[PDB]
Image (cartoon, helix red, strand yellow):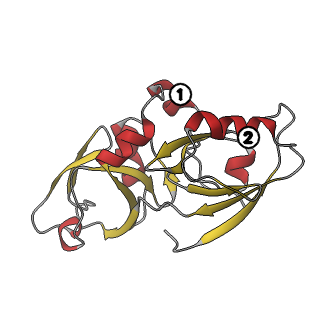
Amino acid sequence: IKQGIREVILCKDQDGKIGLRLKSIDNGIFVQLVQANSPASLVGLRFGDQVLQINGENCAGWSSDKAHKVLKQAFGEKITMTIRDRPFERTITMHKDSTGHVGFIFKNGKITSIVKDSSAARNGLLTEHNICEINGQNVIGLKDSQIADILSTSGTVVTITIMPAFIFEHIIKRMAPSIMKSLMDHTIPEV
């Protein structure tokens, strides 16, 4: 999670898609879903990202509807965006013990309990928090067992990006669970 406002240049695919859905939150515009194999995922937009400008125009107080309209119109040749990195989220680094645990209970991706004398405890992991990423891979919409599997298949170091549930639940609203399961880019970035 950068303190960074950064710039991305986006290019519509052949179908006129950039693979993005945006959502109005507290008078900003935030990324609600980034699609696998999209211009948006290639240029490295992330769920939780805030779009400050599109083609030099300020997003403050746009409705979701309008931001979708703005994107639809733009000459797909070059859409430029100004992005603040996942402002509502924080990262925590943890270390698995000998048992290979980091010490929490989560349920529907929401953390619900911290285990005494765990790495999770030492690091001040919080409950009422939705897991957004693990080691920089988006895990939103995956089932808990799949999330569990990623934590198993992980190094001894584990990195989790988390978002206050009230905020997460207001972001995903109006997005069908299946869309999230199927289309939200759950891949490791490309180089």
Q: Is 35 positioned to the left or the right of 170 in the image?
A: right
The structure residue drawn at horizontal position 46% and vertical position 45%, both measured from the top left corner, is 139
Q: Residue furthest right?
A: 77
> Which residue is more in the foreground, 131 or 6?
6
Q: Is residue 185 above or below residue 51?
A: above
Label 1–label 2 contact, CB within 8 A:
no
Question: 10 Å neighbourhood of mark 2: few (<14), some, or many (≥20)?
Answer: some
At label 1, the amino acid type is Ile
**Where, by quadrant of the figure, is residue 127 drawn?**
bottom left
**Where, by quadrant of the figure, is residue 155 drawn?**
bottom left
Q: Which numbered disc covers residue 179? A: 1
Quadrant placement of the C terminus: bottom right
Q: Nearer the viewer, mark 1 or mark 2?
A: 2
At mark 1, the secondary structure is helix
- Is residue 122 at least partly visible in the picture? yes
Residue that badge 2 annotates: 71
**Where, by quadrant of the figure, is residue 15 drawn?**
top right
Q: Position of residue 100 (x, y in %)?
A: 28, 61
